[PDB]
Image 1 (cartoon, rainbow, N blue to C red):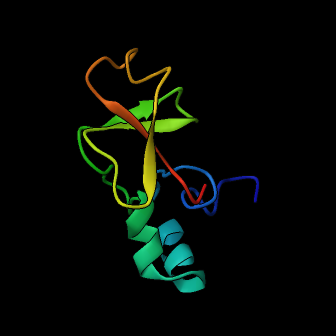
Image 2 (image 1 turned 90 degrees about the vertical axis):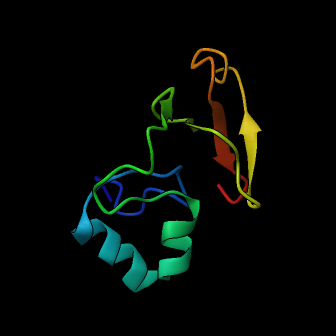
Length: 86
């Protein structure tokens, strides 16, 4: 891969671009792509990553994830959501 041409259900969830997004929708399926937290260049929300690799600081985890910590308190207010499929 070199560049995470698949930065979500197998890693965490990253914002990249349309070329990357399309590659994932084309290979996997749009639903999982926009499910776990990929982004077609925009970032999900004000939410930002923690450890910039382990999990993403979010306000609440969806029905396919779990709150991870260590970082939830370094972020302070946000919940380091790390999807369970990952």
